[PDB]
Image (cartoon, coloured by chain):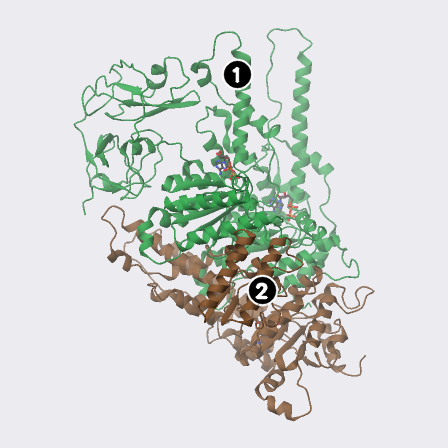
Chain colours: A brown, B green
Amino acid sequence: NGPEIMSKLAGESESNLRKAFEEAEKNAPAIIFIDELDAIAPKREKTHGEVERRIVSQLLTLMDGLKQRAHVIVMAATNRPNSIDPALRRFGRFDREVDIGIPDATGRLEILQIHTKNMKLADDVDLEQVANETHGHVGADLAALCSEAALQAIRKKMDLIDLEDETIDAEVMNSLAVTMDDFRWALSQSNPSALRETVVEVPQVTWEDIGGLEDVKRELQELVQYPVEHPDKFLKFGMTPSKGVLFYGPPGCGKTLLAKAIANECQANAISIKGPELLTMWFGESEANVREIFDKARQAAPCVLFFDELDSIAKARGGNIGDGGGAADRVINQILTEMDGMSTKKNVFIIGATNRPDIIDPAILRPGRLDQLIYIPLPDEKSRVAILKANLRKSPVAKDVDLEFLAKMTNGFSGADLTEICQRACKLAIRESIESEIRRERERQTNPSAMEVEEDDPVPEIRRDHFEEAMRFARRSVSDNDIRKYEMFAQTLQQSR
Amino acid sequence: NRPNRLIVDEAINEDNSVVSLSQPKMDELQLFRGDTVLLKGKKRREAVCIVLSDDTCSDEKIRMNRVVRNNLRVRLGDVISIQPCPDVKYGKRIHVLPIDDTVEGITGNLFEVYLKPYFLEAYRPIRKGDIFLVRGGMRAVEFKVVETDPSPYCIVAPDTVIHCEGEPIKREDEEESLNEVGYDDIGGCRKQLAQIKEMVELPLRHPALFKAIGVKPPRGILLYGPPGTGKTLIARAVANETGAFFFLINGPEIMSKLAGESESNLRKAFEEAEKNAPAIIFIDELDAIAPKREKTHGEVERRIVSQLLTLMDGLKQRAHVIVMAATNRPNSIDPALRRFGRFDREVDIGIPDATGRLEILQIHTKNMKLADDVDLEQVANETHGHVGADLAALCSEAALQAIRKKMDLIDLEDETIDAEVMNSLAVTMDDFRWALSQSNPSALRETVVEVPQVTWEDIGGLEDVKRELQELVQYPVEHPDKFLKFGMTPSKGVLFYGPPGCGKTLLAKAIANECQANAISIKGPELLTMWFGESEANVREIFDKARQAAPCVLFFDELDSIAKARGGNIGDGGGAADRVINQILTEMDGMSTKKNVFIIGATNRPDIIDPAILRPGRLDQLIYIPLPDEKSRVAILKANLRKSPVAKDVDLEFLAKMTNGFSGADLTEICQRACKLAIRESIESEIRRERERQTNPSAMEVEEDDPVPEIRRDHFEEAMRFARRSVSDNDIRKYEMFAQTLQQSR
Ligand SMILES: Nc1ncnc2c1ncn2[C@@H]1O[C@H](COP(=O)(O)OP(=O)(O)O)[C@@H](O)[C@H]1O
Ligand SMILES: Nc1ncnc2c1ncn2[C@@H]1O[C@H](COP(=O)(O)OP(=O)(O)O)[C@@H](O)[C@H]1O
Ligand SMILES: Nc1ncnc2c1ncn2[C@@H]1O[C@H](COP(=O)(O)OP(=O)(O)O)[C@@H](O)[C@H]1O
């Protein structure tokens, strides 16, 4: 342990390190594990104290002595690979770095199942739902969640049942059961999520979650799967597979879902860097974050490195013409450098979404980086119908709804505007259910009847009235001038620059 | 199963040897309040007391106070029997004697003054061995009943005699000091106190029970907040009441000595806590011991941090000790400290609200003889920026001012001070006013985290907006099942746009109050401070504070302030996105909706804000706050005038009908004008009345009459002649065209 190592005197710390390495060598085959390696070994320019540098060098010498004559495998734990000394990651010392990363929904489910193996939990736990809901919790976070649920169950049972009856025995403790309410309380009130950085997981969005864009779906399936599913075919021909594609079109057409679905189809991790992240890196003057973003993408091979709102920096630094400056940006420049430095064979695909393709720098459109400019058009009747079918698969909707008619009213409506249509109508249905419940609660409370319960669900689905009200509320998706701009940009895919 | 035994609980009545029980279990035992009843307790002691029937306490639970539980040698959670004793007697002389050093440094015939009024018409049942108590004269003292002429227990009578003599005798080693901090001494952190209770009850009260199971306990508690918010007081009270051994590890005390000596002291403290399991280790000023790892310059400090980490890990692997820590900010301490297993749960002590400040003041004035004009509700409502120990210093300053007014001016050459003069001291409202004004530094300047006092009645009009906001906020949190039933994720944000002065801030405050949710209002000054200072990372801990105060309404007043400082409508050649707005967007994207933390944004210029904040999932609801119409203006005037006394001659409907297109805050400015004119009229009338009769040397000539206690229509007419149109009609047209363009944009 890093704290255990450098907790003692400098000479004592070095002696402890040497003794540990000698014991591991004596007990070969043995594993040396150094958690919090950044504590022992910080960056060489950052390690202020001479004692810390001496400890770093002692560890380096001990591991080199293991390398020359031993049979011990050294493992280390750190928050970031760059937080430790670069000399540690030198070849021969730390050749292979394993990115433990974060657990996905399936991973969180597995962790919860592991922690509930010895926990008597009820049938309402539905750990699939908990894991799907759980975000930002990694490993020990889920362990603390399970511990909190168990402790809440114990405080509900022991603190309220066995007070003066008789001393606690095994019968009462083995009868304890953990319910869904305990897990909900642990999720909501008593769990700090320690994860705030980029998510590295296979997204749950599939092709069925996207409506329309069949040609775009097929083209993206080609450009992604074919290099990775048929490498022999690409190697046979004298063409290097493309390692990037750009999505341009009106906002709300599902470019983010396109990236998520293509990542899911290949079972590849997706790292979606939205416009907020790009603007955070630009405003903070820290373009070097793109370096470890691309490192995370590469370490998660196969990966779909999605850059949502790639024009966010070009939009913050002026509009169409903007200021007197050009279109290149420091974070976009670092992205270009990383993509140029990224091998195509690494099967890490870069997808960029731009709501204003005309404001992005053409340098990102050069062949070899984002040569494919896939246009995501505004959905037509069939695409809108498919989008509505995909969205309504989750919210229970009455069969009286007429999706084809609804699409035919919605002229030039984007997919996310159709999801906002459900936001309106489905929310109206939720409000109707809530108000019906409260009025039903209030109406019979006046009558002092011991047995008078006319129990009936008001409505469990969404009727066409809610959708009509949403139509009366929700209006045209986007301006026609924007659509004309997109269509002229598509018409000018060539004969430019 | 023997509905005679019963379990313990806290008490409300302040009287001693008094109890209260649920209403149904009065026939089960078949005895009424006047029935004097005996109760059993360990070490073979049983004490008789009066009885009562209440409601709050459950059938299975009793209420009583430390005065009785001490002599009973019983603690909470324990269980006791009960038996009526109608055979009690009107006791005669029953000998007593003060049992403490409390008598140290006292004089005067305490007997009468202290006892007779308490024994006045009381019929306080007594049994030998009682340790009853009485307080007065800025002091508190107790006496033991050494003898009961009839035994073992009797009633007191106003006729019974008291030959009370002897000298103060000593507290046997069985007596337990009440000096230990208690939950009664904690105010302003009721939710935090309950969280701490539910965290530490199982590990401490049930050590063997938890040892039976194989769950991981919370062995690291990070009490973070402003200094002086009772963190060490909370820890001491929790440890003392739960019976856990409290070790006060002080950061300055730790690293005051040599590095090796500091590490040895830390190891010895941890070993002693482990030996005294269940024990509580508290480390106040943890940032002193454990700063940020990149910031800890000295190697000795890093070594101490690592030693603390190793000691707490050793506690985690093999011990039964709960570690608590106090720091100004959670990020000020080393991030390795907050690692899972070491400090899993961080409790935000925060700041006390108006009710919390009231509770703190009541706690600090419990032993303070204070007059009836203190009106601590008014003091707490006025008190802002004072947290915990700040209110303690306020009470101390008021008491010291009272003492300097009485002692320094009364007893100078008469005779040496005795108990009679000191117990006659009273604290008045003027002392509290002086403490508030002249002699109190408010140490709080950051964001306020409290439930705002503004309610729906405080807002006039906007009934549709009120209903929509009530839906969007309450329904996700009051009916989660309904939202989960449908396939729609509840919205976690709403944007308020419209002319300034329509009450968007009050809308956020009222929706926070209706849900009883904390409101953190980040105004335009805060946004511009974060933007100009190039510190966008402040939004991170702002959102952390909002999340830790779940349910919370995270209000962003003047969300367009940064977009307005960085140019006007078109502004410079740059875009609309801003670094602080970008950090807000990142935090909202990283904020789970289930966390029931709602973000409300107010923009007086919705057209200048970046559309990226209007994307669905962050602020998809754009609620328009229109300029109030006749009915809305009438309601606004009714809400505002409820505080300022106004004469019934005022005509609010007519006033609203004159005010065409007037905002709510412009109506409050209308009161500013007219109500201020009324105040000035009252002041000038008072001064002219003072000056007019001073010329006549009349011993008795007082034509006392209030000039005007209310506000007449003349003041409002003068305000109308002064106050003019609210806002330009062009702005209203811009707002109406923005509302018309809610869709078909971008
Ligand atoms: N073609 C589509 N089919 C199904 N769902 C869609 C489609 N387009 C968008 N959505 C959903 O509607 C919402 C609005 O889309 P949005 O994310 O704005 O699209 P983009 O990422 O291209 O800007 C998104 O949350 C997305 O999940
Ligand atoms: N919430 C509170 N309620 C009552 N008293 C308080 C509160 N907070 C602080 N105090 C008073 O302040 C005094 C010292 O404050 P302290 O607890 O040392 O501050 P900190 O929390 O910074 O350690 C105590 O004597 C205590 O009576
Ligand atoms: N509709 C209203 N009803 C009652 N009081 C209001 C209303 N609108 C504003 N006020 C009060 O009048 C003052 C001016 O309002 P202001 O805060 O400028 O509104 P906003 O926060 O929307 O800009 C505020 O102090 C507020 O307390």
Residue position marked by numbered label 1 in the rendering:
B406
Residue farthest to the left? B87
Whether residue B686 is visible here, answered yes or no, is yes
Foreground residue among B283 and B188 = B283
Q: Is residue A333 above or below residue A159?
A: below
Foreground residue among B550 and B381 = B550
What whole-number distance in Å separates the C-alpha atoms at marks 2 and 1? Answer: 77 Å
Image coords of residue B427 (percent x, y): 50, 23
The residue at 70%/38% (across/down) is: B720
Dot 1 surroundings within 10 Å: few (below 14), some, or many (20 or more)?
Answer: some
**Mark in front: 2 vs 1:** 2
What chain does badge 2 belong to? A
Of the numbered discs in the image, which one, if any, rests on residue A94? none
Image coords of residue B639 (percent x, y): 57, 41
The residue at 46%/23% (across/down) is: B369
Foreground residue among A289 and A244 = A289
Q: Of the residues shown, which amino acid type is indicated by label 1? A: Lys
